[PDB]
Amino acid sequence: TVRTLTGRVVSDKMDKTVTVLIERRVKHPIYGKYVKRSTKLHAHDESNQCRIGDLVTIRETRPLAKTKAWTLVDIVERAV
Amino acid sequence: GYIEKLVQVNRVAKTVKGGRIFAFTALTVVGDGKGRVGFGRGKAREVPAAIQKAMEAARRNMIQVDLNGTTLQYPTKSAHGASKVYMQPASEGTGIIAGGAMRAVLEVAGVQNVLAKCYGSTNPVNVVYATFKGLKNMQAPEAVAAKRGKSVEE
Amino acid sequence: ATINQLVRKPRKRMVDKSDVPALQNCPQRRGVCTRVYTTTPKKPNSALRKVCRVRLTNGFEVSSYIGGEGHNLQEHSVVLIRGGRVKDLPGVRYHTVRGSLDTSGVKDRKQGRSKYGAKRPK
Amino acid sequence: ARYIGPKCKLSRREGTDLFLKSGARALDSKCKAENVPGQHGQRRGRLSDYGLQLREKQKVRRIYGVLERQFRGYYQEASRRKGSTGENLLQLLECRLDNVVYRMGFGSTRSESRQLVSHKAITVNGQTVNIPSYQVKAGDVVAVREKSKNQLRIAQALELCGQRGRVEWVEVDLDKKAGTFKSAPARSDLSADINENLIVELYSK
Amino acid sequence: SMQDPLADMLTRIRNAQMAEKTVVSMPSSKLKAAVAKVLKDEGYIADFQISSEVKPQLSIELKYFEGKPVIEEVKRISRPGLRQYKSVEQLPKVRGGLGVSIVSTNKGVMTDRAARAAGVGGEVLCTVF
RNA sequence: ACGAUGUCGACUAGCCGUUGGGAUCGAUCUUAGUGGCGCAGCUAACGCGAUAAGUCGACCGCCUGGGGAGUACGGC
RNA sequence: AGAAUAAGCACCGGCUAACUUCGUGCCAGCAGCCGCGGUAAUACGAAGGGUGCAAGCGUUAAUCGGAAUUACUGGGCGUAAAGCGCGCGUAGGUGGUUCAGCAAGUUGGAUGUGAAAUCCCCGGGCUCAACCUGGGAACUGCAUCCAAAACUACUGAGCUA
RNA sequence: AGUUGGUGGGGUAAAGGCCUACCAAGGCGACGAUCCGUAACUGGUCUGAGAGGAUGAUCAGUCACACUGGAACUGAGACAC
Ligand SMILES: [Mg+2]
Ligand SMILES: [Mg+2]
Ligand SMILES: [Mg+2]
Ligand SMILES: [Mg+2]
Ligand SMILES: [Mg+2]
Ligand SMILES: [Mg+2]
Ligand SMILES: [Mg+2]
Ligand SMILES: [Mg+2]
Ligand SMILES: [Mg+2]
Ligand SMILES: [Mg+2]
Ligand SMILES: [Mg+2]
Ligand SMILES: [Mg+2]
Ligand SMILES: [Mg+2]
Ligand SMILES: [Mg+2]
Ligand SMILES: [Mg+2]
Ligand SMILES: [Mg+2]
Ligand SMILES: [Mg+2]
Ligand SMILES: [Mg+2]
Ligand SMILES: [Mg+2]
Ligand SMILES: [Mg+2]
Ligand SMILES: [Mg+2]
Ligand SMILES: [Mg+2]
Ligand SMILES: [Mg+2]
Ligand SMILES: [Mg+2]
Ligand SMILES: [Mg+2]
Ligand SMILES: [Mg+2]
Ligand SMILES: [Mg+2]
Ligand SMILES: [Mg+2]
Ligand SMILES: [Mg+2]
Ligand SMILES: [Mg+2]
Ligand SMILES: [Mg+2]
Ligand SMILES: [Mg+2]
Ligand SMILES: [Mg+2]
Ligand SMILES: [Mg+2]
Ligand SMILES: [Mg+2]
Ligand SMILES: [Mg+2]
Ligand SMILES: [Mg+2]
Ligand SMILES: [Mg+2]
Ligand SMILES: [Mg+2]
Ligand SMILES: [Mg+2]
Ligand SMILES: [Mg+2]
Ligand SMILES: [Mg+2]
Ligand SMILES: [Mg+2]
Ligand SMILES: [Mg+2]
Ligand SMILES: [Mg+2]
């Protein structure tokens, strides 16, 4: 299936665009402790239907603006 | 057993009204190359008397260790004061990769392939203490089997 | 140090500084003598050591030692200097290579006459 | 290069036989091998452990006549292999072509065996070899060229080898001056006085 | 504040075995019960029991053989500050095989021998010799 | 600004005082403090020793030869 | 055809293998560090005599090692350098016990990739070696599937230490 | 402040603030933005028991430059050794 990422929406001020934060756990090369890193992605939300704090998923497409190449596929769960 | 190796000779001095009084300290080890070994130290006015006293001390309190044919049983680490010592068994072609006092103790003790190293202070007396602590406490199999049969533990 | 303390900032090596700042990574350098003279050593030893002030092509002005019993250096002599610290003298951090450009080596030298640039007796 | 000059001075310094002459008469009644060379010969001269390792290494090197760079190359390549590199060194150093010519009886001393090899007089398998380092394979048939097959030097070396013991791991047909090397000698086949692990300890520092 | 209770188990056993006691009792847990079962099956302790009544108590009796204790060195490897995991071929060998390394795998808690035979890795809980 | 000894939790022989307070039959037990000794263990040694500097776990602060120097410059 | 055409460099108090004499007299000088030299200097400069390397031998510059002396493997903080003057608390780190689920870490396997050379193993060809070269191993990583469920994470329901 | 996003249009072999006119005020940053100094990168090389540390000569892959600063033309391909 299509490779998909999951994250939390941290900004929706832009029109038809959201910002999604994605966590990851990376092992230290030398000290061997898993440390927590984050990534920020700009995602194309055509219907402007995503509020802040939601848990959503996104997939890679062709660029639609500069530094914007991911489009969301569904809302896994909505922040209350 | 009788295989004598002299580890250290040192000159020490006390003070009295009038000046200094000098003495000599000798540290030696004695064994047979078949497992038994001991160490001794001696003070005297001149070197030969100190060496003889050290040899006589070493002949007393000579202990027995269990070894797997010129080599140790398992890698081990031991310490005395601020001296630390690490040893591990080696294959047949290896010599005795050890320094100073450790080499003497192991040559006399009958091992031949030991690949040893030491950390911290390298005072010969404390290093020999640490090496005897390490060798004395080796267990050998069918003795760690003090619980059950052999080859079910291994 | 706890693992978290090392993760936040790891252990660092402080790079050691060279004891021959002149002659940057060069085994030896060419210079010209500006003043040859004699100086006295520190307290335990006692002699009259022969040294020369040298201006180098790097532009540094340093002080070098002149080894061997005799020498023919003068002011405006062009010399080759290598590294090497002289314990007895304060500030002398270099040596003058004998028999290289204008130092001519030592004479009546029979034992180890390669450190002092002496030809074989032949 | 090679060591040149007094071939008994090494024996006097080392303190043992160190076969370096024909062995016709003796060693003691040539050079009084009981004092180290020089003015100071009667000194007790206790020498530290490093001295012991150095003497043992120099002793084997002078026995087989190998310079330092080549000796360390042999040591490294023997350390590469498996099975007690300490005796691998002896196994390999015992397979040199000049040494094999020595132990077949063709030369009284290693120096003249090397002279014979370097002067194009030995065919390993019908092919001429003129270098004193060719590691002889197990099962080779060392021979002497026909032109030099009738020299008096080889004959003299033959009866000199006649009383030297028998190595028994090579076999020589003396009538036609042919030789065959079956296999590298085992550790017990060599002299049981040299302790090779001491050298291994030396290079491991 | 009871950040790591298996280390508390091991330390209790070590201290009481160092004080020539014969019974060690502590609060119980399923992981502790599994480790104690491994210890008994390997022969380093004589027996263990588990109590009842809502706050169960785990009890262990110790072995001495000679005048020395049997467990002469036990140590905690995967603490909650490092969480060591190992593959099959990298499972640590204690004292050249004369000791044991307790490993938690998807097939249960076993020794390094059993995991090496079963060809499965896991988390290295503690080492015993 | 000192116990020249970070905070939190769990285990490990004992004896003798004292402060606030409970239970059992003046004594015994028990609880939170505050002191003097002391077995194991630890330490280079002095010494610490249930108020650990012993055996462990969680997190934090700091050290890397002596002067120059906790000083100069910059910031606050 | 004819032994004919072809040995030098450093060092010798200790570390560090190898020692005696002659000349100097805190001078001339040596030195990597301890240090040596002021009338018997194995430390200076020469001799004999040795010791180590060898068509090379020493010095200089630079890197790692030894250095567990930045200590993940693998150190410390009462008195040697080192516990903030003392609280509260944000981000972060860590988390008592039982049941079930999940499948992110975790573990095992498969597939794609990780250029060739290089390093490594077994061969082969140069008279051997250096050198050239065939096959394997290795590249400890990443992505995609399949399987497992003890531990950590996440979800739900509990319990009282 | 073409700065982040959107709409109509232009432009490119091709997605795209690549360009433009309007619309909203967005976007990045103690998980180190911005600035300063230094530096081609990798397979690899030297060390080390290993973990690591230093480094990027020869050989091979990629990048950039061609007296200095700009610009385009021809062409399948250049902003051209
Ligand atoms: Mg658009
Ligand atoms: Mg773009
Ligand atoms: Mg030290
Ligand atoms: Mg220097
Ligand atoms: Mg050569
Ligand atoms: Mg006060
Ligand atoms: Mg303070
Ligand atoms: Mg404390
Ligand atoms: Mg406490
Ligand atoms: Mg006390
Ligand atoms: Mg302490
Ligand atoms: Mg400083
Ligand atoms: Mg100030
Ligand atoms: Mg002040
Ligand atoms: Mg100020
Ligand atoms: Mg000596
Ligand atoms: Mg000198
Ligand atoms: Mg004299
Ligand atoms: Mg001299
Ligand atoms: Mg250097
Ligand atoms: Mg260094
Ligand atoms: Mg290091
Ligand atoms: Mg550590
Ligand atoms: Mg320290
Ligand atoms: Mg305080
Ligand atoms: Mg504060
Ligand atoms: Mg609080
Ligand atoms: Mg707080
Ligand atoms: Mg919190
Ligand atoms: Mg949490
Ligand atoms: Mg569960
Ligand atoms: Mg896997
Ligand atoms: Mg490759
Ligand atoms: Mg499942
Ligand atoms: Mg605009
Ligand atoms: Mg547009
Ligand atoms: Mg540059
Ligand atoms: Mg190392
Ligand atoms: Mg670089
Ligand atoms: Mg170039
Ligand atoms: Mg290239
Ligand atoms: Mg030019
Ligand atoms: Mg231009
Ligand atoms: Mg065109
Ligand atoms: Mg171009």
Image: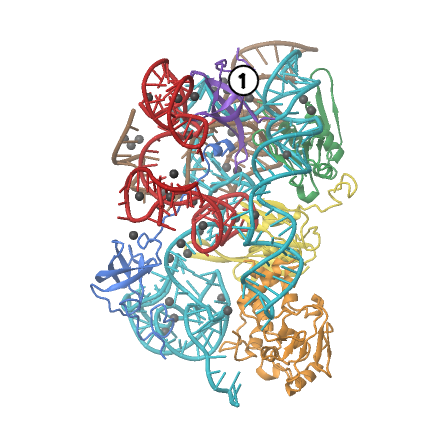
Chain colours: A purple, B yellow, C blue, D orange, E green, F brown, G cyan, H red
Total marks shown come to 1
Q: Position of residue C53 (x, y in %)?
A: 24, 59
| Residue E63 occupies quadrant | top right
Which residue is pictured at 34% across the width and 52% down the height? C19
Q: Position of residue B50 (x, y in %)?
A: 56, 59
Looking at the picture, which amino acid does disc 1 mark?
Answer: Leu
Q: In the shown orientation, is residue D84 left or right of residue A43?
A: right
Q: Is residue G83 above or below residue F23?
A: below
Q: Nearer the viewer, residue H66 or G45?
A: H66
Q: Position of residue B84 (x, y in %)?
A: 56, 46
Please, what secondary structure does the residue beneath circle 1 have? strand
| Residue C73 occupies quadrant | bottom left
Check disc 1 and report the residue beneath it: A55
Q: Nearer the viewer, residue E66 or C68?
A: C68
Q: In the shown orientation, is residue D176 left or right of residue G153?
A: right
Q: Chain of mark 1?
A: A
Placement of the N terminus of chain A among the 4 image quadrants: top right
Within-10-Å neighbours for mark 1: few <14, some 14–19, many 20+: many
